[PDB]
Amino acid sequence: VYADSFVIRGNEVSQIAPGQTGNIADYNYKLPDDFTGCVIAWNSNKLDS
Amino acid sequence: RSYGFRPTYGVGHQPYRVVVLSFELLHAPATVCGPKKSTNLVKNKCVNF
Image 1: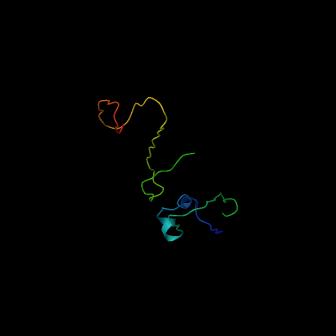
Image 2 (image 1 turned 180 degrees about the horizontal axis):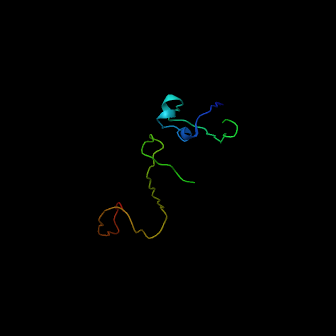
Image 3 (image 1 turned 135 degrees about the vertical axis):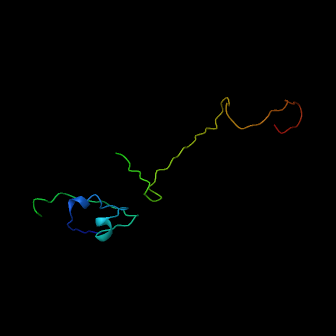
C-alpha cells in the first residue's frame, strides 16, 4: 500500500491526474499512464492559511 | 455515471465500437443464409442430399 501527502495550491488540484502537463504536472508531481487506485482530496483553507 | 473519452488517452482507455451477432441452429423454417442455388429433386437413387 502506497501513501503520500503534500500541500499545493487549489488551482493545481485538478491537474493531479495521469496525462496532465504544465505547472504542477511537470515541475512538482507526475504520475504514470497505467496508474491504478484512488485519489482523495479535500479543502484545508481554515487550518493552512 | 458517465465516461470521460478524450483523444489524448492511450490505447486501452479509448472508446471502442463493438457489434455482436447472435445465431440459433434449431429446427424451424429457415429464412436467411448464404448464396447458393438449388438442384432438381431426384428420388430412388443413392445421392448426397
